[PDB]
Amino acid sequence: MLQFHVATLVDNDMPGMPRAMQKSGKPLKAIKARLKGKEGRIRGNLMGK
DNA sequence: TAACCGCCAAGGGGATTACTCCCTAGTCTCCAGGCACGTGTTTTTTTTTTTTTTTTTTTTTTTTTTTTTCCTTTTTTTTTTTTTTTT
Image 1 (tube, chains in turn orange, purple):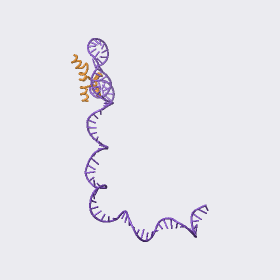
Image 2 (image 1 turned 60 degrees about the horizontal axis):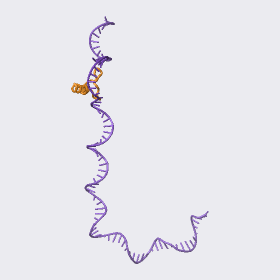
Image 3 (image 1 turned 60 degrees about the vertical axis):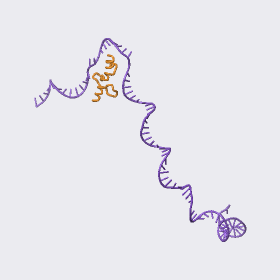
Image 4 (image 1 turned 90 degrees about the horizontal axis):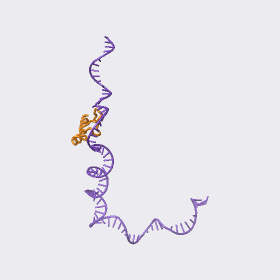
């Protein structure tokens, strides 16, 4: 479970790995979700601020 | 009905004796295939690296702008206070 919490802190988009459960019925938004994506920290905040 | 026996007749060829002769038994002497020893080159086995297709993983999906709506927990177990009954 410690490895599960560490992995979901790092990457919650890993297939074959149980998704982290948030309080509002959503998956947890990890740091990879903050960076990778069109609306991410790179494309939506550094590329397109 | 001709096997078998008795009787008679005839002849054919194996046994016997002698002479010969010739092929093998025996004995040297030279030499060469038959055999004991060593080994091989194909045959099978095992690795080794690649090949080729299948399967899985992962990442991706034009940009900008303006309005609402709903939600931003919830049941389920444990605890703690309160109230009632009894001696």
